[PDB]
Image (spheres, helix red, strand yellow):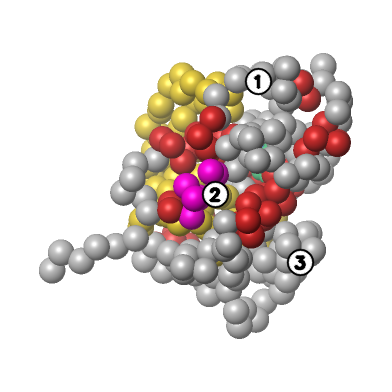
């Protein structure tokens, strides 16, 4: 019959979370198969020694993923949906589809939280020049992206009529001592990362993909990108506070 189907690039920024990944892959694969979502998991493995930069990794994963994927899911590796009514569907013309809304997320409950699991059309992501590159270490990168969404004249949509709440919609298995949040600030990080970034994004992220690995986990194919991010210490020296 030849019908076209939407295809989701599941982008998972990643470093030192193997145990999480082993739970993530079978869970998401089963979950998405149940709702018939065609997709592939890309593990975006940061292999430079700078601080963790999930936003730049997402930009890299976006560039790498084939054009056949017409939308992406920017997805934390430790955050699993427990409710089948969370549809990972092709977002509407309105803008990004935010799965892990503040009324459903176990921890983050502010109105404009768009983190955890955020689905974006290829065209919309392109239109916004992707994510800022200036976020090294934990925090703020999704909040700046929220402003990009608005500046592009788009809106965030979230699932409606979800009956579960903050305690039973997602599993967030992330112990703050086990997997520490890198909240250090150095140089003028605080002042700079709190400012909207009109200068960097998808179009100027600097990197090399050193290696592409094809992995199977219990028969499920997953792609690993070993990504070497570059840091310009003349611009973002807080990529390394050592
Ligand atoms: O050293 C790290 C740090 C993070 N991650 C990945 O990045 C994801 C998000 O990082 P955290 O789990 O450490 O932070 P939070 O639990 O506070 O998550 C929220 O805060 C982050 C702010 O940086 C992101 O916005 C994220 O989407 C949002 O759900 C992780 O799940 C994991 O997939 C790694 O792989 N290695
Ligand atoms: Mn987490």
| 69 drawn magenta | no
For the C terminus, which image quadrant? top right
**Where on the image, by quarter, is ligand 1?**
top right
Instruction: Report the mark closest to the observer, 2 or 3.
Output: 2
Residue that appears at 65% across and 81% down:
163
What residue sits right under mark 2 in the picture? Answer: 128
What residue sits right under mark 3 in the picture? Answer: 111
- Of the residues under marks 2 and 3, which one precedes in the sequence? 3
For the N terminus, which image quadrant? bottom left
Q: Residue 74, percent across and down?
A: 55, 50
Residue at disc 1, secondary structure = loop
Where is residue 130, by image quadrant?
top right
Magenta region, residue range: 124-130
Where is residue 229, by image quadrant?
top right
Q: Residue 161, percent across and down?
A: 61, 83
Label 1 to label 3: alpha-carbon separation: 32 Å
Q: Is residue 46 left or right of residue 167?
A: left
Instruction: Report the mark closest to the observer, 2 or 1.
Output: 2
Judge the density around disc 2: few (<14), some (14-19), many (≥20) Cα neighbours within 10 Å.
many
Number of dots carrying numbers: 3
């Amino acid at each position: 019959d030849g019908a076209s189907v939407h295809k989701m690039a599941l982008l998972v920024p990643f470093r030192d979370r193997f145990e999480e990944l082993l739970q993530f892959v079978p869970h998401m694969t089963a979950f998405l198969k149940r709702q018939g979502v065609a997709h592939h998991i890309f593990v975006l493995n940061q292999v430079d020694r700078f601080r963790f930069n999930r936003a730049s990794l997402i930009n890299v994963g976006f560039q790498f993923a084939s054009d056949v994927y017409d939308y992406i899911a920017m997805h934390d590796v430790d955050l699993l949906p427990l409710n089948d009514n969370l549809l990972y569907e092709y977002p509407s013309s309105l803008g990004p589809l935010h799965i892990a809304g503040p009324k459903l997320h176990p921890k983050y409950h502010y109105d404009n939280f768009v983190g955890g699991i955020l689905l974006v059309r290829r065209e919309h992501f392109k239109q916004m020049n992707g994510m800022s590159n200036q976020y090294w270490g934990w925090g703020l990168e999704n909040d700046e992206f929220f402003v990009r969404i608005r500046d592009a004249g788009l809106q965030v949509t979230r699932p409606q009529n979800i009956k579960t709440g903050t305690n039973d919609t997602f599993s967030h298995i992330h112990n703050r001592y086990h997997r520490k949040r890198d909240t250090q600030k150095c140089f003028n990080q605080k002042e700079m990362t709190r400012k909207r970034d009109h200068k960097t994004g998808l179009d100027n992220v600097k990197y090399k993909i050193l290696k592409v690995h094809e992995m199977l986990i219990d028969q499920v194919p997953v792609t690993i990108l070993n990504i070497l991010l570059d840091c310009d210490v003349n611009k973002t020296p807080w990529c390394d506070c050592s």
